[PDB]
Amino acid sequence: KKISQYACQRRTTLNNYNQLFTDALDILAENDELRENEGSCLAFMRASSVLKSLPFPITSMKDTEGIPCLGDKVKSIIEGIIEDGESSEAKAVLNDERYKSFKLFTSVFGVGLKTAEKWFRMGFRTLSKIQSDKSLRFTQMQKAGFLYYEDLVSCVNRPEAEAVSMLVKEAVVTFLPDALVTMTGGFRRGKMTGHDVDFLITSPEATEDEEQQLLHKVTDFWKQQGLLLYCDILESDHAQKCFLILKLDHGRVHGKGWKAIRVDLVMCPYDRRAFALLGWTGSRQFERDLRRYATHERKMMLDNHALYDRTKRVFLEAESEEEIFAHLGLDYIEPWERNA
DNA sequence: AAAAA
DNA sequence: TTTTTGC
DNA sequence: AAAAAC
Ligand SMILES: Nc1ccn([C@H]2CC[C@@H](COP(=O)(O)OP(=O)(O)OP(=O)(O)O)O2)c(=O)n1
Ligand SMILES: [Mg+2]
Ligand SMILES: [Mg+2]
Ligand code: NA
Image 1 (tube, rainbow, N blue to C red):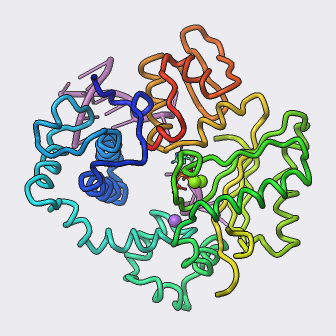
Image 2 (image 1 turned 90 degrees about the horizontal axis):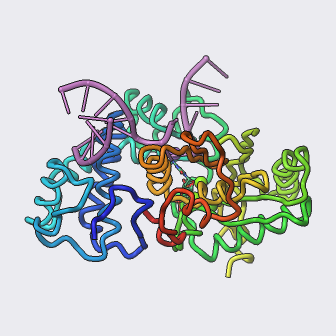
């Protein structure tokens, strides 16, 4: 069986037999993201992804024969881990002051690569020193990121994700009773934890205006209940979406009595719900490779809204994810097998 | 950093 | 070798 | 007026 270089042609389940290798490759990838080396970052993410798909652990260099996305640099890293159970390259990154600061600072909601680099060059090394500084000015996103830091840093579990699903569905059906709400992201792929809870909302009978107002109505409703801790709505991925922080009462889940949860809502037109569901189910790596496969192997363009055939100069229709896979000439990969 | 063009 | 990497 | 939310 020839392992494909594309995550969309691999079944990647949550039982990872090569976490010793992939934890090291994930660290090296993250460091290349920080050093703005996009190419080397992507090569380590693809190597890590292919090893996550293996149905067995790598125990010798012979085991890497025929595996794609493993060049000489990556094979040197694997060799070193086989040697003593550790990666000297990943260990050097874990001890690097810039890397430590970037991981720590970007762990705050509202802090990305640019702000983390700025704070590092200002001489900041701890979150306590950043928060207590009287000259720094924080965005509304960063204020929320610091205020709900401990809750957001400890990730969401499945009872919490299910409790959030109930809250989202309850709010959405009050303004659109025919609306279909689907939990997407990691949790749809069978993950037991996640940094956030994502939802795809669609309605078969809503108007263009009704579709536009739903996220504003749902967030105003939560604001009135005192459950909206943060809200950023992006007007109509070109679909209308919102990045939220919701107050999840402990009583709803099967101290302060509540937990701050990162929630993302995406609203899409009913017809395009298969493309949106596919795009928002992920994983990130699965999505990139789906689009890369479509471009390089089928001369097709795929995105969260549509599938276009560049040769035939026609858009291809789909009522399900299965139909999208069939258009692309791919065997159907179940959501729990997309953990690339 | 790896594979395609 | 140069180009591409989710355009 | 970037910058984050990727
Ligand atoms: N750079 C990205 C980020 C997100 N997504 C898509 C696919 C994953 C989906 C979910 O967004 P995330 O929450 O960032 O992904 P995740 O699977 O849900 O991871 P987590 O469980 O940690 O939230 O959106 C993507 O295609 N590319
Ligand atoms: Mg998610
Ligand atoms: Mg998300
Ligand atoms: Na962040």
